[PDB]
Length: 101
Length: 97
Image (tube, rainbow over all chains, first blue to last red):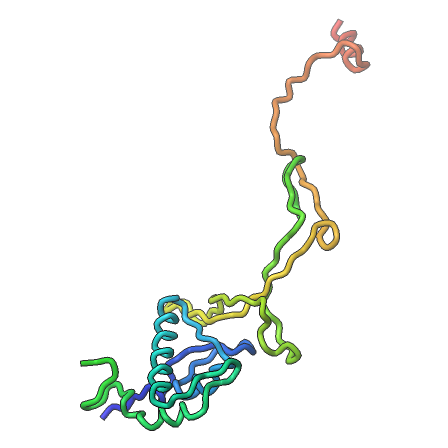
């Protein structure tokens, strides 16, 4: 078949504070969320990216009851929780798809 | 700093925009640095990447010296009013006489 997961494959372009632009995946993004910045040419693109990130954080907090703290990369037990349900973030799958019908 | 005419108004401050500079002491981007999307990669399917941008200022007289314009700007017809007192005309008149 065709395999493409949000976490496994690099699809978010960011820029680090050291001046190096890069494209990374979802698992690397929230692992180092305190050392980079989202960089999108169209402002609506980065606004919707931030909104989806906030909604995902809200769901994971609702299912882990951990409140994020400032200056931390992210609260612990969020990356393993997102790895628990990695099949849900599927694109070009067979029966399970993300944001599709 | 070139000028163009005599009463050309001038600014006391010259703002300048500069690319950020690495060096591993301030390896992280400073607080007063904005982000510009002007790092070119490709042109036909145009591709641009972010670049950190810093701002500074300059003052005329201490860093840049004000220059002066060259040539003549305002054009006027010659229209020389005749004079009957200088030596050259006084000799030309006698030569004609």
